[PDB]
Image (cartoon, coloured by chain):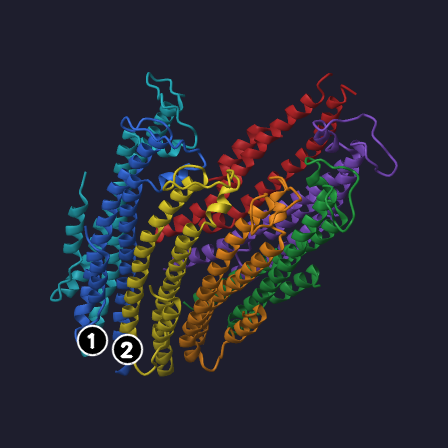
Chain colours: A yellow, B orange, C green, D purple, E red, F blue, G cyan
Amino acid sequence: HMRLEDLQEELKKDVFIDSTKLQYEAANNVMLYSKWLNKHSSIKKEMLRIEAQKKVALKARLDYYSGRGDGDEFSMDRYEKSEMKTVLSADKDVLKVDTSLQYWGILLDFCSGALDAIKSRGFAIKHIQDMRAFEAG
Amino acid sequence: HMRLEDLQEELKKDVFIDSTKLQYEAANNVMLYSKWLNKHSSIKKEMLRIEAQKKVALKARLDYYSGRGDGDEFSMDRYEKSEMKTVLSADKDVLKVDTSLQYWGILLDFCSGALDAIKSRGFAIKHIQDMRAFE
Amino acid sequence: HMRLEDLQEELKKDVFIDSTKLQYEAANNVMLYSKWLNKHSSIKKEMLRIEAQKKVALKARLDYYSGRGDGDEFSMDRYEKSEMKTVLSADKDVLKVDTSLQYWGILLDFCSGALDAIKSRGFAIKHIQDMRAFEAG
Amino acid sequence: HMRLEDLQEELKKDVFIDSTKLQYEAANNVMLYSKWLNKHSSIKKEMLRIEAQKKVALKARLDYYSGRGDGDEFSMDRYEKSEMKTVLSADKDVLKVDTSLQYWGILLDFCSGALDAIKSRGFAIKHIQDMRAFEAG
Amino acid sequence: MRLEDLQEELKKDVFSTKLQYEAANNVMLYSKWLNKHSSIKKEMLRIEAQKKVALKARLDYYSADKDVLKVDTSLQYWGILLDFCSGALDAIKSRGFAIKHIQDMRAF
Amino acid sequence: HMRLEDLQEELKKDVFIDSTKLQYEAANNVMLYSKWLNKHSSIKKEMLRIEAQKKVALKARLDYYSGRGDGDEFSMDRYEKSEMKTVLSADKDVLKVDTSLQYWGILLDFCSGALDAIKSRGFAIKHIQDMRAFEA
Amino acid sequence: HMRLEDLQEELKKDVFIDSTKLQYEAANNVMLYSKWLNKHSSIKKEMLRIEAQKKVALKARLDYYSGRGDGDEFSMDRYEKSEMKTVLSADKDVLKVDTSLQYWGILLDFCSGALDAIKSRGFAIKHIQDMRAFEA
């Protein structure tokens, strides 16, 4: 289980550009894109597993609250169809799984932004090179 | 708990472009994007925690008003199903949590706009460089 | 309490483009976006406070009309459930708060349009620059 | 009280594009957007005032027809709950206010379409510029 | 007016020898149909108001026998006319997209 | 059935640029694009087959839960129309097929990013060549 | 019906650059673009015919399941409006036509990528030529 703050610090380090090694950064920029692309794809792989758990968790707990069988356990609060969306989204089991799924979703949205930065950093490097050539004439 | 006005002043400072250091701003523009991207992602992390509280807070207070048990406390006003949406959204506990969640939502929408500005500032810098080359 | 007409005149001034200082406007366009983004975000902060008042105001006056207690005051008109939506939306206290909330909503929708103009003004400036380069060849 | 036909003629004039001054129209297109955005926002400000009147007008006349007090005046037709929606929507006071509110609603929907045209006119201008560059090669 | 003229008007505008003048006239066609769409809505507002008062008249039968049926009939006519203008506004919006497609189809 | 981690390691190897053979990498960059383009297209071919299974799997299990016939088998839980979307998305057969489809979807989105990297790597190589000419 | 793997192998062959005949490849690169442009356009011509069949196939089978068919066949499962999208997308006739249409869609998306490679290969050749002049 990786942390968000670990990715934040990692991105802040990778995004930095070395002005002295502009030729190095140009080839390394495409390398950084591959690293986060691996992270982004791996996160979706994790979310697919969690979403599968959430889908089952909902149906399982839906049976519980709606009076059906969820492991020989039954809800006695007798919730109506209108009250259902509120109760399920607040269930201890459901909320635990969903919170997990949504967290990796934030990590995924971060990697999407990370790739956006790298894709624009590669343009930034090429732009800087054009600025150096501008001083040359 | 960070404030909105603190982000407003921070963005207004970062968005400013130094005409003398155009090469510096080009590399720094991508740096600013990473800073707000960290803020944006961290806010969602906070909202996920608050939303979880709100989800439970609703179900807890729903039991209270609907005659069910919420810590051996019961509502005696006997609200109907039609009146429910109005009462819950005005509950002291619910409104307190929701207001918190919605506030960070404004902060999140601000960071989304901040990233939009930076993404266009990087284009603005490159455009200015093309204007200098035009002369 | 800011006025709408004050924002209308402010936007009309900011949106104007100086043809002589195209390089200046390009960097200033991103600056204007930040100004209205601060306004837009601040308005939502205000609306969140007002909406909170409205939510309570409704529940408070709902008790009043439905025969429940609203500060030892009771409605004697005996309104039915069907008549309720009409009466509450016309209550002096409710209508005062809602009108306030809806007003800032118009201001918010104006800032959203203002940001849309600035976002397209930045494209307009870049387009004009491309038109000047077109005359060059 | 502005008229619809006045806005129709105003829009038809603004939407026209000068082929000789393409650079001028590009900067002026963003200016026209600000003009109608001020109109659109101002109309909503007017509707908010009228809607407030309508909300009260309904509740006031609701008391009248339902046997309650509306300025020491009472309806003797004894309308039932089923007949209420038809009677209120045809009341002289209510219909007068609603007609006003709905009219500015048409003006508002026109400004929304006007902004849509301007937003696409800015794309039309940029497209035309790309067509001129196409003949250049 | 007539529905017939509306079909001949739209089918004639939807259609190259002067591409720069056709792209600048695409927003012009929009204004011509925008003023038309809002004018239909204007005439119906008067009709919809007369229908309400006529609906109360039919209700006061307990308190021409079908006056509102003469109003609702003409009201259902403009509804068709209003739905044919919404397609036009949806067409010109797609015509500008089809006009931008040609300039992209010529460079491809 | 190919793995994601196998593509991750493969991309990380291909994306690397040899500074000594810049002329070689320029012609090889367009070659790498063709390789992943073949992968990307082949994955869509696989997904089209799986999606077809999923479409049938849904309709088959929909009959089961809604009281209709799914191979002489019937659901007795009597689920309502509101409960349907939740139950179907959690069915053992459906979830198995969907998980498969979504997985190749991740592989497909990875190839799309891989092609994006190669398309920008070709620009990176040309940029580096322009930087070497700048020193000249 | 052409195969995807046949196009994959064909592209992999065309994309290769001969370093000895750089002048030849420069003129041939524009030739390859025309070849795939003919393929791309021809595929759309095929898809237009298939899409027309799909449009009719849907409306035909829609009548069947909804009971509004003037034909001899009627569906007795009595599907509701909510269940309709799932049933139609899983119909034997519909799924057969759609699968065909989607397949050529993959071929079309491949040709679009092929043209992208050729368009960048022409830049790759010119870049390599500039690299040879750099050594000069």
Left or right position of D118 against F16: right
* Residue at 67% in and 21% down: E69
Chain under disc 2: A
Q: Is residue B1 above or below residue A48?
A: below
Image disc number at residue F19? 1
Q: Residue furthest left?
A: G20
Q: Residues within 10 Å of mark 2 (few under 14, many from 20)?
A: many
Looking at the image, residue E2 lies above or below residue F133? above
Residue type at mark 1? Ser
| Amino acid under disc 2 | Gln
- Residue extending furthest right? D72
Q: Nearer the viewer, residue E90 or A29?
A: A29
Q: Which residue is at the front of the view, D118 or G82?
A: G82
The residue that appears at 76% across and 19% down in the rendered structure is E61
**Which residue is the site of mark 2?**
A23
Other residues around mark 1 within 10 Å, as few (<14) / some (14–19) / many (≥20)? some
- How far across and how far down the image is residue A58, in percent? 40, 45
Where residue A66 sits, quadrant-wise, is: top left
